[PDB]
Image: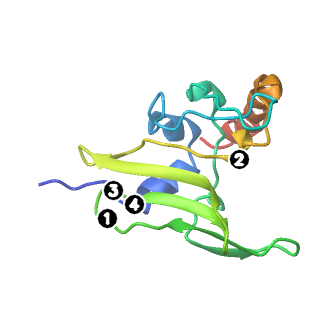
Amino acid sequence: GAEEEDFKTFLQKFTSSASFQYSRIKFPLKSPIALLKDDGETEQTFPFTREKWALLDEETLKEGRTTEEEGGTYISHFTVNEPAHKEFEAGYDESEPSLRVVFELTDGKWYVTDCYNDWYNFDLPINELEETIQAVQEENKAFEELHP
């Protein structure tokens, strides 16, 4: 009557199809990027659009915990059990996250509505940013050429 797309199965596509990944994501996103104007305690916001995305893997969007030698417990999961209103968090134990992905389900189709990624983390003065954008687009080509 509805038969909605599955929080598992939609993800399997998301991690293995580049154009589909992009076709699922809003433009712009509700998280403008926000960095420091090379002055310390200064506020700034950037338009989040398709041209500054970072593609994401199955070992990015998994539900589990990992171990580095030199960090600690890294977690990745959805934190929120809802039938249509789930979102995703990755980060270490006892610490803040750095990969945030809001998901929403309308019309029986999932659509990603927000983003957080360390590719435009706080340690990134706006002066260098337009090169950071282009660098993520290097890695993105190497993904999407091989993620059909």
**Residue found at x 71% / y 47%:** 118
The residue under label 4 is 7
The residue under label 2 is 118
> 54 or 131, which is in the foreground?
131
**Residue found at x 57% / y 25%:** 47
Of all residues, the one furthest to the right in this rendering is 70
Mark 1: amino acid:
Glu
> Where, by quadrant of the figure, is residue 72 drawn?
bottom right
Of badges 4 and 2, nearer the viewer stands: 2
How many discs mark residues in the rendered view? 4
Mark 3: amino acid:
His
Q: Which mark is residue 85?
A: 3
In what element is the residue under mark 3?
loop
The residue under label 1 is 82
Of all residues, the one furthest to the left in this rendering is 1
In what element is the residue under mark 1?
loop
Mark 1 near mark 3, Cβ–Cβ under 8 Å? yes
C-alpha distance separating marks 2 and 1 = 26 Å
In what element is the residue under mark 2?
helix
Neighbour class for label 4 at 10 Å: few (<14), some, many (≥20)? some
Mark 2 near mark 3, Cβ–Cβ under 8 Å? no
C-alpha distance separating marks 1 and 4 = 10 Å
Please state, as top left, top right, bottom left or bottom right, where the C terminus lies in the image: top right
Q: In the figure, is residue 66 to the left or right of 110?
A: right
